[PDB]
Image (cartoon, rainbow, N blue to C red; front, side, top):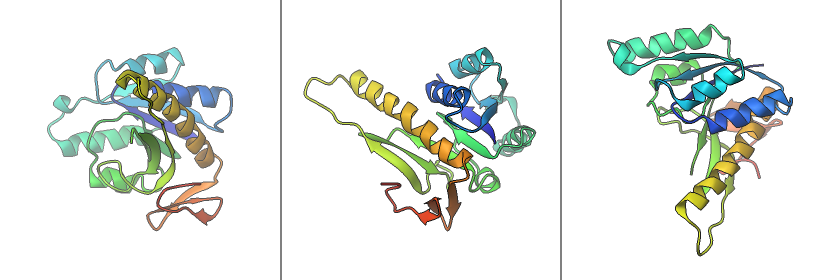
Length: 188
């Protein structure tokens, strides 16, 4: 099970995925990490784990089209069974979304988190799993995030493990776990 992760920043979600794989909680291997931001910290986490990295800068190409074609060609050299977006800030082309249909995931910082199968250009599509984070009087916005971030590091690797296992699929713009079509709110 080949996993390719796309990032734009820090890479803390990427790290949680790397760790879940290292402990075999995810029956898969992160084969490469792609960044559209030069020197994103996540590239460093990938290097530290001995994973190949590639950076593609928009200003380095003639157009969005040229960029998207190069990104797809490069990702494809790694034969991904799953392409996971973890903080990848670029608006995707319909062609990219179509090319990875059924194997493109995204984690959404929305208080709660949710991971979806991406079926549109803004990283949207059917919800697979989501959780809620409670707030309390006294909570600092940086207390909220930390809780949310902790939550993301927990559910993304879990959802990816379902995929790596053959248990999770996308059909009719819906998510199916163990052959059961999940409801709009994901697995409950």
